[PDB]
Length: 448
Ligand SMILES: CC(=O)N[C@H]1[C@H]([C@H](O)[C@H](O)COC(C)=O)O[C@@](O)(C(=O)O)C[C@@H]1O
Ligand code: NA
Ligand code: NA
Image (cartoon, rainbow, N blue to C red; front, top):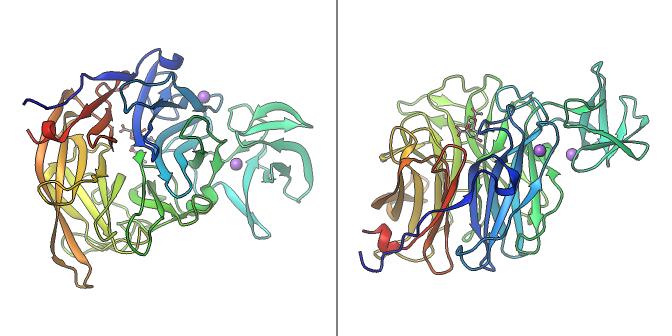
């Protein structure tokens, strides 16, 4: 229709960009200053997930609303097939700090062979990263100084990137397949930040000790973006979606969150904790032993009164949605299935929209509208209150009033952002692992 805007797709990442053969897992965020930040997995040896790869994090910035992009940069690189995989972007608007979080594996590990727990150990009241030598002997890193199992200082020290130094000389890296001392083989949540709108980034912070429990096997970023809560008693809280597996390997969604500008983090309950399944059964993410109720990758959006809605990848064939009245710490016992929104077991994206649509508050949603990874569709969901819960909190439902096909053919992971002009930017997996595509869409297009 006249006035509609749907730009010709541009390959924001692609074979050869930054000398990476492959790319996957898009993330896209407009900062408060108005810059677009796009992060991606730079997969160096094919499209495969960890451990069968060597994956780095890359970033591109646009300062003119997505029309042109900078030459990019690798911001996280571990050696020897130690991977960083699945990034997520959020900003603290009060301090102007941008956060990027990612899952990290030592060489040879990934979601299915991850060992149990955080890989940290408590000594006299402080968590310390554990290291292991060839014979199984366990060490701790105390302010980057390696102590043996008798709290004897050794000759070894580390840095944030895991380099291992013997008397101040680098010999290896605790994440490699060859280091004399290796970190525990498991998932780690890593955090970097930018104070200059994304131009430069800090070294990775290993926050596993605050968010990974003893009984979790894998705990990883649910890729895409986070939020900072805008209304109510938890305003200012930074919410980052995650998901984890238990001993039996079953997956459950959650968010980690910080109320002190990213300094400390906690993990909330999963919507699977005390979940009431359809016919009344009560399960828990800790004990979950069946595949059916699994909740995995997810993204979160805020309702007008500050209530949280977690959109979750799952195994029912349809979108699943959890609700939290307490800023992400727990969820209502009922997980809703929207049979208006197919979910073929793939990552999805959902963001708040800043302006009313047809007089209603709205969200924007992206995913493959099929039983396969195809038929990529952006939707406008209008929020309606439909009564209240027993506890008197409002009950919110979505009306998927506008549904627009934007990518025929292959469509997998995606990430949305609202643009300074009020339009919608989208970075999506239009190929399985090569070209990653960026387009801009106005609501006139989406409503057509
Ligand atoms: C492997 C990983 O850390 N992330 C990958 C994730 C994951 O393997 C999938 O969610 C299943 O997780 C679990 C714990 O069973 O899913 C993808 O493999 C996919 O596109 O299906 C891409 C993504 O990078
Ligand atoms: Na690397
Ligand atoms: Na560390």
